[PDB]
């Protein structure tokens, strides 16, 4: 049944709650972003109002074939009325089109639902600064102190320099980047840019990218694999067998693959710096796992919450075990005591 942490008290609203059938008493279904665990259950047969960003609305229409009359896109950073309740969508710094939602309840309570986010100090100067938030529904994916990772910028720098060195040493090397959802486009776009290539990909992936309002996108991507030296493949094919196979498909145009797997966290982060990352190599194939995250680190999450000073926190991730729930509640209390709210 719909869990309580997907329901917004005092409204008829749910968030990211499309796989429970008809939720009893729900007048509007919000969708924070186009990732499968969140949209699971939507299709062309859905007949309730869906509220989301413009980009998420492009993907609903084009990829899932939801009918237009049920898609209600909202502009960001703008006070809007939905079924008699004031709401605002804010940028979540996750994947393209991903938002956080502020709800202003009739009784005067103010609720922020983060959806999926990567907390950033720039959020401290949005419309959030302007009033108090009583309740926070929080993306707790990496709510534990072992979870450190570099900035997105440092990671991209590493990848650009690595790729550029490799292809300049060997002009017959191919670069491959794995993907399995939207997000992390910067990785393959930045590499293609330094190499003066377009990124080549399947027709399904090209369609998905054309929904995302990325400026100058027609200049950066293509379905002609033959004219590109940066290829995108399913994350599943980023392994020695899948890459050898793919190399055979290119008709002796290339004699070496350099491949990137943008993972979330991996335990080499506990010890190793970005400068120090090394690939796994077999023959003429090398695979780099790079820690490019679109979720808050533990420290970024802590800073956001200590800034916001919420009266009550409701976690939306890692809620399935008592040991996780208990550990999270302990961190929330430390943070509260340290900051004095
Ligand atoms: Ni997500």
Image (cartoon, rainbow, N blue to C red):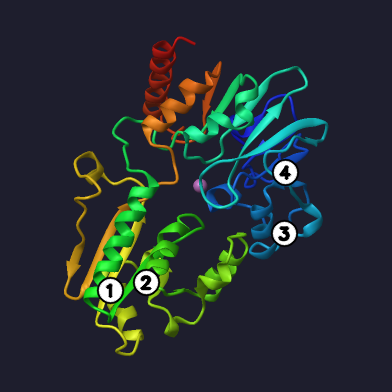
Q: Secondary structure at mark 2?
A: helix
Residue 195 circle label: 2
Q: Is mark 1 within 8 Å of ligand 1?
A: no
Sequence-first tag of 1 and 3:
3
Q: Is residue 55 above or below residue 309?
A: below
Mark 2 crowdedness (10 Å alpha carbons): few <14, some 14-19, many ≥20 = some
Residue 66 circle label: 3
Q: Secondary structure at mark 4?
A: loop
- The residue that disc 4 covers is 22
Q: Is mark 4 within 8 Å of ligand 1?
A: no
Residue at image position (51%, 72%) is 221
Label 2 to label 3: alpha-carbon separation? 38 Å
- The residue that disc 1 covers is 167
Sequence-first tag of 2 and 4:
4
Q: Position of residue 140 (x, y in %)?
A: 45, 33
Residue at image position (42%, 64%) is 188
Residue at image position (77%, 47%) is 49
Sequence-first tag of 2 and 3:
3
Sequence-first tag of 3 and 4:
4
Q: Position of residue 31 (x, y in %)?
A: 64, 45
Q: Is mark 3 within 8 Å of ligand 1?
A: no
Q: Quadrant of the N terminus?
A: top right
Asked if the residues shown at circle 1 and circle 2 are in contact, with their CB atoms under 8 angstroms apart, the answer is yes
Mark 3 crowdedness (10 Å alpha carbons): few <14, some 14-19, many ≥20 = many
Mark 4 crowdedness (10 Å alpha carbons): few <14, some 14-19, many ≥20 = few
Sequence-first tag of 1 and 2:
1
Q: Secondary structure at mark 1?
A: helix
């Amino acid at each position: 049944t719909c869990p309580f942490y997907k329901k917004i008290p005092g409204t008829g609203f749910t968030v990211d709650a499309f796989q429970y059938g008809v939720v009893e008493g729900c007048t509007a279904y919000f969708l924070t972003h186009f990732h499968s665990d969140h949209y699971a259950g939507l299709s062309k047969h859905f007949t309730f109002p869906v509220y989301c960003s413009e980009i998420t609305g492009n993907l609903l229409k084009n990829k899932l074939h939801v009918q237009e009359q049920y898609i209600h896109p909202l502009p960001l950073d703008t006070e809007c009325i939905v079924n008699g309740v004031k709401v605002v969508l804010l940028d979540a710094n996750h994947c393209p089109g991903a938002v956080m939602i502020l709800f202003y309840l009739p009784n005067g309570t103010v609720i922020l639902h983060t959806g999926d986010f990567r907390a950033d100090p720039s959020m401290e100067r949005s419309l959030l600064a302007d009033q108090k938030v009583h309740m926070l529904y929080l993306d707790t994916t990496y709510c534990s102190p072992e979870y450190t990772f570099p900035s997105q910028q440092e990671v991209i720098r590493f990848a650009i320099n690595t790729a550029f060195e490799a292809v300049t040493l060997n002009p017959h090397a191919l670069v491959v980047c794995g993907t399995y959802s939207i997000g992390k486009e910067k990785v393959f776009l930045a590499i293609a840019d330094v190499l003066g290539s377009k990124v080549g990909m399947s027709q399904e992936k090209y369609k998905t990218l054309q929904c995302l309002n990325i400026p100058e996108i027609n200049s950066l991507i293509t379905t002609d694999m033959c004219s590109s030296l940066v290829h995108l493949l399913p994350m599943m094919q980023i392994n020695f067998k899948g890459l050898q196979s793919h190399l055979k498909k290119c008709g002796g145009k290339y004699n070496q693959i350099l491949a990137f797997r943008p993972t979330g966290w991996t335990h080499s982060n506990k010890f190793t710096r970005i400068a120090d990352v090394i690939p796994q190599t077999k023959g003429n194939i090398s695979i780099y796992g790079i820690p490019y995250s679109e979720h808050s680190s533990y420290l970024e999450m802590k800073r956001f919450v200590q800034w916001l000073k919420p009266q009550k926190i409701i976690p939306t991730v890692n809620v399935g075990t008592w040991k996780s729930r208990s550990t999270m509640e302990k961190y929330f209390r430390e943070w509260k005591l340290e900051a004095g709210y």
